[PDB]
Amino acid sequence: GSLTEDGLSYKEKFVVRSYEVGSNKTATVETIANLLQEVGCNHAQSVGFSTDGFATTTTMRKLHLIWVTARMHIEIYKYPAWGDVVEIETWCQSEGRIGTRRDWILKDSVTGEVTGRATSKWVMMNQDTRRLQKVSDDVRDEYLVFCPQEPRLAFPEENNRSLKKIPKLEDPAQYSMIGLKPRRADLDMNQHVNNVTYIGWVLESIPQEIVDTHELQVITLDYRRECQQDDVVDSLTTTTSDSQFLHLLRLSGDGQEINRGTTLWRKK
Amino acid sequence: GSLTEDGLSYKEKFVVRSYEVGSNKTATVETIANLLQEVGCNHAQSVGFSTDGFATTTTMRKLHLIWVTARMHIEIYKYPAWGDVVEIETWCQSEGRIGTRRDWILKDSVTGEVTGRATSKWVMMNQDTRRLQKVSDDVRDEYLVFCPQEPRLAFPEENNRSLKKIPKLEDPAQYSMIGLKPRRADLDMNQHVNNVTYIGWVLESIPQEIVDTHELQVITLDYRRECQQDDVVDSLTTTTSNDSQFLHLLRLSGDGQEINRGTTLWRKK
Ligand SMILES: Nc1nc2ccccc2s1
Ligand SMILES: Nc1nc2ccccc2s1
Ligand SMILES: Nc1nc2ccccc2s1
Ligand SMILES: Nc1nc2ccccc2s1
Image 1 (cartoon, helix red, strand yellow):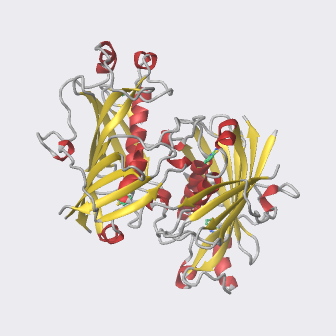
Image 2: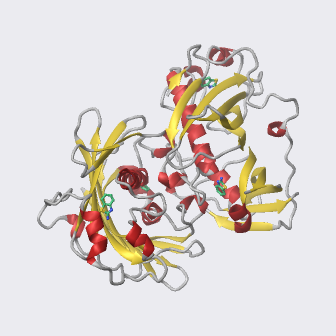
Image 3: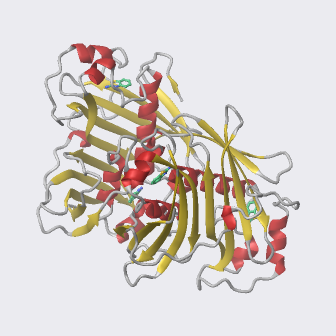
């Protein structure tokens, strides 16, 4: 992988692995999400950020502040096949004091055609208290030099799918998968549940008949609270419609919400 | 990746990814096992085998026969760090009519030092009946041309660990993790639980204090029966031992049917 000529975006190529594909011999949406995370990490490394946390400047590290995902939105037109090379370009852009957006564009390396796109919203949070505290402009000044200044949007349109409000699923859900728990492979280097695990948990309550006859086109996921290594999760899904679904992840006991989302699927 | 000059082994380099590492910022043993599987698949592809199944000749495919893992044994001296390049060489060898062995050697790409080794035993099974049924010599003839003829062992030692018999853990287990179930990410392209998932399930019952103060040096795992996508698994571990050794058992909650047994060896950090 490498930073582009202007130093304001990063590109990397990935050869799709045998264990990374589903029944259609194409990459799963969790494999895609893992590659988006990897290219994001390599972009942070390329611009001088340390391996300590993820994209924290020395000022954020001093203040015990970290970046946390509030939303992930992924649209895939074609999933890359096993052995194919997919090229991914990523960049970030400030959205004022609220937070930062990281965008991605996925391409077929042979044809140069855009096969997918993604966007995410990130906020600054104190790692110890979990509060989105007052921070001050001197922190943001440190990041601005690594971002393009003119707007560069993977989803440029005003009021597009990536910015839509997601409602809360009401009981009874049409489908459910109960008692989901993370294992050691689901944890990151800091012993926190990796963000991709929640995508997998959302998709666990989609009926097998849908997975067998459709392809996932769009997934939008909000992140409200983390699942601790000892928490247990219930995955709920209701058809709202192409087939569209509303999703809710909540802690098995008291029903505390950890994520909400929507998926759009097209017939194969 | 590429076949070597003599066409009898295959080598591939992997850059360790951010999500592939544990707390020490080095590759987990499940990341290693996934890379061993990947280099094995690329070796099969390089010698003409189709993307249909795994290393199945046209004769095996006609007879509805597949290769299935009976044992995996991995020994790691140093786990590669995040961003490091690890080079892995793999090859296969017939062990008569019983089955075939696939071996691997892992090296640090910068120094050329051996950082790990692995071996596995594979058997032919009918995909439909799950029987290890009678198969003629014409099937084996098809594979012999892709294997070295002189013995080439990743584990040459006399009474080496890779061939030791594993006993059955007796209740009560010292530690356990109950109710483990696979999710869609744990399945392969044929909707079967990936062999690496069972390694993860075995390691779930190792106490957190061990994972925090030790590094996994050796894991030997026997595969007796598959976990179906709707089965539920219990992971049991008992200490058998500076080094810590454990005996492991995976069994279905449904009635206690054994799916795997194994042992692990850990060294203080
Ligand atoms: N492309 C798809 N990836 C996944 C991952 C998990 C479940 C369903 C699907 S469909
Ligand atoms: N919050 C931000 N983190 C990064 C990392 C790499 C490049 C740009 C930015 S802006
Ligand atoms: N190197 C190690 N890999 C793993 C994977 C799962 C649990 C424990 C360990 S120690
Ligand atoms: N059973 C065997 N499968 C393969 C795959 C690649 C090379 C050699 C062999 S022998």
